[PDB]
Image (cartoon, rainbow, N blue to C red; front, side, top):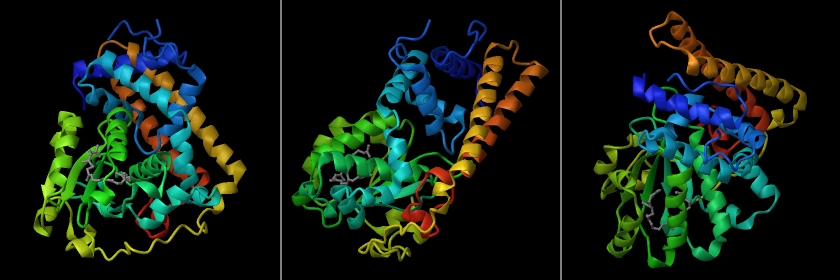
Length: 357
Ligand SMILES: CC(C)=CCC/C(C)=C\CC/C(C)=C/CC/C=C(\C)CC/C=C(\C)CCC=C(C)C
């Protein structure tokens, strides 16, 4: 649960959003903000509620709030920035999946997929999804930076779908530097991935494991550490053997070649053959799932305004507003689970059994 002055912050964030979306609310008892005055109401509302998939609305907003240390103005500024930069580009990326990338012959993206440069390999000890990155497979010439970035965004988004109920909604990254050479170094995607987690995926990082760093990496590290904010810097751990990795990941999830028990094929990529995509063009059922969502979003907005202006926080009526918000939250996440087979092309992880939405 949340404290009173925390509840106030969360309500003020919702109130700024509601003034942008023309949802009637009175914020006095707990005129569009500068951060939102240059956004399109319709576009923002629609994109915001598409990007909510498996997380409740409150949790999605609270990620931005904590990342900005519970300062309401800074939180609404970061959130407006994100909404401006996201539009519908990332949702298109995750919904088209690897299939769209192949169908439109995006050669650089494809080479990153086929090299298995970044792959979700299971969960860490807190049930966060774990991304295995192997920089020794990287060559700046293999792709454009835009392709590299589109691939990175796709992998990040995929790992968001692995987030478990009642477990931290964040991704751990294992950087295996075995066989890393300057041949492989590329400061540009480092910078992008620092910049993009900082402004677009608040509170989405769990652990940053840097495994068997060779000596040539220490000067590079002296640069990269300068670019990090202190919380991301707090997340980084250097490990040198499998016993150290064991403290963060269960042996069933660590690749065999690292000392673990995971016998996944890391040298041969198996793209999604598309045979689980049958619901992608049941258009009418999709439309009925999306109408359910539209109604559940309207109700959520309604009750959330109610809960914003209601005084006091003792009240039995307040108890009912809170419980209704939680049940509408639950209903929205279940509705997204139902909608998932109908908008999203299946990933290699839906096929190999590892992912269930
Ligand atoms: C999804 C993902 C993380 C990867 C996309 C593909 C890329 C960018 C892989 C290549 C990585 C690379 C070329 C690195 C060279 C050596 C550098 C490092 C191991 C340090 C880079 C990582 C960091 C520790 C930066 C700060 C952390 C984050 C993620 C914000």
